[PDB]
Image (cartoon, coloured by chain):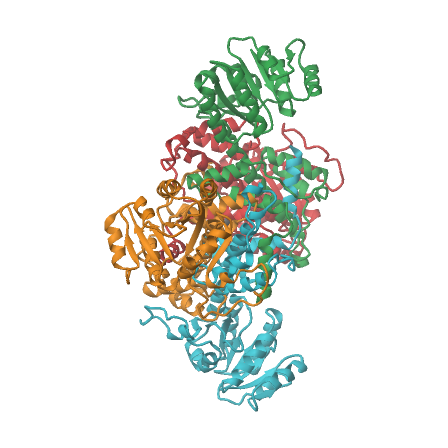
Chain colours: A cyan, B orange, C red, D green
Amino acid sequence: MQIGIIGLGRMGGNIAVRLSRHGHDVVLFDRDAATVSKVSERIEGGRGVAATSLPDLVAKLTAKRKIVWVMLPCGEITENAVQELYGLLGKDDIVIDGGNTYYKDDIRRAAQLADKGIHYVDVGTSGLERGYCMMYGGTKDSTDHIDPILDALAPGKGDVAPTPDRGKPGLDPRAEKGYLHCGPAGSGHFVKMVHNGIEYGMMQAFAEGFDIMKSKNSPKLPEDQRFDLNMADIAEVWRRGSVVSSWLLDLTAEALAKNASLSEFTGEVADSGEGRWTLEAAIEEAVPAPVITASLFTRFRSRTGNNYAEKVLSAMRFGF
Amino acid sequence: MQIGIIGLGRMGGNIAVRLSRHGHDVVLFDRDAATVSKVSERIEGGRGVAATSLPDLVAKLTAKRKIVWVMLPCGEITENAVQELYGLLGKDDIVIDGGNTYYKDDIRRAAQLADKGIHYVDVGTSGGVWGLERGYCMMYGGTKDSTDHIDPILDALAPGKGDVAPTPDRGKPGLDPRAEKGYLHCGPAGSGHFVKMVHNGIEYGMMQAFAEGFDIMKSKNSPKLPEDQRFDLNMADIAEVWRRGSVVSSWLLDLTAEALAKNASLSEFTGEVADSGEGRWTLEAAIEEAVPAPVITASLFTRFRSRTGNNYAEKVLSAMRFGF
Amino acid sequence: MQIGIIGLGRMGGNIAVRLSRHGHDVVLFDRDAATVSKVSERIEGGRGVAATSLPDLVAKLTAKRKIVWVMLPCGEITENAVQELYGLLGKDDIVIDGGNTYYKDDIRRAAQLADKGIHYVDVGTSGGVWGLERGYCMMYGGTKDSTDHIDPILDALAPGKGDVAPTPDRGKPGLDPRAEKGYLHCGPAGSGHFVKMVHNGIEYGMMQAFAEGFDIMKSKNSPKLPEDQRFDLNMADIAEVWRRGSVVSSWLLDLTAEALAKNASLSEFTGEVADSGEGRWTLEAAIEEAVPAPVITASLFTRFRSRTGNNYAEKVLSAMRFGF
Amino acid sequence: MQIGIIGLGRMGGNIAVRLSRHGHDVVLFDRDAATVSKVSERIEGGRGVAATSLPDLVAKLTAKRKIVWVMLPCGEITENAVQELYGLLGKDDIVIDGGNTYYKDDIRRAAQLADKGIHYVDVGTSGLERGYCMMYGGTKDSTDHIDPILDALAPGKGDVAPTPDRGKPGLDPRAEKGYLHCGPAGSGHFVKMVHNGIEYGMMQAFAEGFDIMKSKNSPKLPEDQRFDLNMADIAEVWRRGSVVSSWLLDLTAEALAKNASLSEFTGEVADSGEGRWTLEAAIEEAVPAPVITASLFTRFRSRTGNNYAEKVLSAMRFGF
Ligand SMILES: [Mg+2]
Ligand SMILES: [Mg+2]
């Protein structure tokens, strides 16, 4: 199949390359022509066309149904591209938003684009060589049509042990290949958002445990209550056969082996948006979510010094 | 090597069997003689001997250094066995406590046993489910002399390096290569059960992170939501897709996908969750050390509240609300 | 002064009565004419007039600047009234919204109304229980011109300085002396409902702090504790003793002591706690501003969980635990 | 009555003065003789005796039942005094511990002292002019005996509105005077400990709200979503007729009126012990206590920079 790709950052460029390596043709565009030419040089021979604008890209899509994948900075930039494509595309064409879009915008865009018969698909991704775990929303018609593109990008079943009771109606076998049609437009970015919220919580659980172990050698403790524990070795031993074995643990063991004191790191952690939006979904649904909440607030506080709340505490105490 | 094992519950019996399958001679004891004979039947090649009492077990250990592994219920029972061994063993013998003992008890026991030259080793194990065939992830404390001596025993029980990708940049002093085989000498006595305790605390937090996310997704179809804000999400398929290539890929996720595939409604579970000592003890360590631990704490409190109806705090909230 | 009031529920009717007791002429309207007549009966000295519709209410306001106070259910109902007034009023008239409106709606309404020169004032009130006799603590937003004009109305409704000790060091520029009387111009439109929203968020946290402490004390007699670690504590007397000279002395404590004196078991309350918009909206503001707010969040989540049985998250926890 | 007082810090000295002003005789001791002489000069004429040691103090207590109030730094110092008094006192004498003692130590001391017939009373206090709110444990015999001393120190009923349904058996009228016999030894310091835990939670609730209001003018917000709110005026207006009116609010309004930016404060807040012990009691009892927990953890984190947990988070993110 042929697909246009707008946005050639790390993920957009890699997506184009992996598609071209799996027998699909790509039409490439990015605001920066040097990035366009770099990705063109990375794409398998003759599997690619470079466009110079969005209209030129659309004109270069010659299949019955034009498919355009947008991988742009979330927000106004992605919205601008979507509206321009809304003007340039027509009935049964397909727009895929692979960005970290707030899922409610996906619901809105899909409704607008449907007034012209344009199908909207939101893809949340979690690479070039290993494939992309994908959670996506849209109509059955459009997601069926683009199934070959997604199958090309997905990791496939791999060598992990299969989940035992999966042979039943209601369970989509494509989930075992690492890509899942989650429901209508917006549901893919919604599931990806919660995936990131869970990830935040897992990260904070590990981070707290390692802090507790590191601080078991604290001067504030009496010497006979101290242990001088080896952080990198503990992360490593947990990699094999423990209940906490996980991709996150693997990363932590690599970072601790490099520099166990973590002296090279500030500890100032951003939150990309998905954490906040996960908490908002919890609020909307009256779901208690203390772990994702604690993870988000730890991130907020890591970026400031002492904040006004803490100054209020000191002021109250002094007033005693 | 020859090793005595007292306590033949699931873990003790499995440990005896795996040791014997790696060619070690094991002397078996349990308060219930029928359990001793059940475990003996599982050992092959004559590498198992049934003892009739704890003194008889000790008498059957003929090596220069007697090694006795205690795998009993936490608390008074383990303590009784350790005190009896204090009386029965002598200089350079080794007592291993493999239960989920509170690590401060290990510090006290090792100091006492050192009075007679008896070495005390605390072993914390993870992975008890798949352990017989797949091996045990182990975190253990004690003196270098004794833990060096029992290295073949621990290596027999550990999973080995396996086929996972090796961690980069480990060829440095300070980093124990045995960690890559799944068993780690953590420091002096008590440090093994301390590290295992924190492992469980982290596990609590990871479990709660998943449980919250799945609750949010499940309730995206809630009647309380406007119809046009709902999604009817497939919990088992979402669990499954995250298994391959995602940031939350993990053994806990594998279990969750299996449970959800079996029955997505989780019909068969009440939701009333117990907590063993380790979550509480991890939070105690955080407090002692002035470490913020909101995720482990939230996991513990969620468990507390899952076991009750509305509690007194909530009734106080209602009374205040009525008051204005 | 003359003022129209639309919405004669508990708060609207009480506000009309107190205004009239301070000599203001009030024009009354409510969708239910029987409520209008009930409130009219409570006004003395001819200072109340019953209107028959919102346009009739507006027609009965003969001052240079028409002032209309809207005290209706949050949401579509208040919005309908505000839009109708946008059509009926003109330059320099004043619309006051006294409900618990989401403050972003106040920002939008004030911008729209300024198209016709109509001034919009948001008033957040606290103390609705004792308000008729004791006055209303008020937080309000709008232009200086309009809020200056309605100052006698707000002063009539406020508690006044009373007999509490004055706050030291308030004789400074930047500090509004009206704050000492219990009504504060908080800034532009929306800022009054914003400050009131945060007031309620703090209240949630204070309530939960007390509720947790009382739960800890009540459960100090728990059967799960060893008998020699129990205390049988008297909740109502502990509440009472804290009223005089303690750090937790507060109106919430006064209410709690009263409720516990009435019935210490709190037998009559389920513990299932609702939450109006303000707790959620306070947390939304914290998120927007990247402010950690763990206590307000914990109070909200406690309320969520008080209303359900075991939820899906807890069933996921049970399923994972069974898995190993 | 006559009472010996050991420990003449702020509270010990004030307790001695207030007793002497209410018709009781005090015998004073402190390790620092200059502090002894300062308090002696503050005590009403001839209501006082200065002792030079614990034995001299006990010898100067000539009543049938010797009462000794210990107001010393918690821990080894208080324990040393209690053991020395255990040696010096006898049957039906009374030892009062007014410090911030961990209540389990009170249970232990009371049992030891009872082996000689010495009664042990723990008093938790929450001053000179206004009186002390007191929560105390011990036997009915000893607490009855010292009731005049406690009544002298308590605030009395004052001018606040009386709690309506208080005229019933089971409700101790002394609670309305601001001192409460809480049960056996240890129960007073236990109730005081939870009082402090509640106070922490109340403080953190206010502190969070003021932080939210202060940060409503944040640069990170778009200008049209900002309010520049007056912190001192908001605290003040809430003092009269609001649901949050409280002693803590009064203190906050005074601090904000002095310096609304709170520029003079670090925000580095200690935790004295009661917060931790409250949380431990919650754990022991399987009681969820997220608000007191969040308050304690905010204090822990206010005293450090970025901690090892946060560095673990940065390391994981970089590993992506
Ligand atoms: Mg636990
Ligand atoms: Mg709410």
Q: Residue furthest right?
A: C173
- Viewer-nearest residue: A118 or D126: D126
Q: Left or right: A6 with respect to C8?
A: right
Q: Residue furthest bottom?
A: A46
| Residue at the image point whose x is 38% and y is 66% from the top | B236
* Residue D301 in the image: above or below residue D243: below
How many numbered tags mark residues here? 0
Image spot of residue B61 (x, y percent): 34, 50
- Viewer-nearest residue: D116 or C88: D116
| Residue at the image point whose x is 35% and y is 62% from the top | B23
Image spot of residue A15 (x, y percent): 54, 79
* Residue C98 in the image: above or below residue B257: above
Image spot of residue B187 (x, y percent): 52, 51
Is there any visible trace of residue C218 in the rendered image? yes
Is there any visible trace of residue C276 in the rendered image? no
Image spot of residue B136 (x, y percent): 40, 59
Q: Left or right: C208 with respect to A77?
A: left
Image quadrant occupied by the C terminus of chain D: bottom right
Q: Quadrant of residue C139?
A: top right
* Residue D257 in the image: above or below residue A291: above
Image quadrant occupied by the N terminus of chain D: top right
- Viewer-nearest residue: D262 or C75: D262
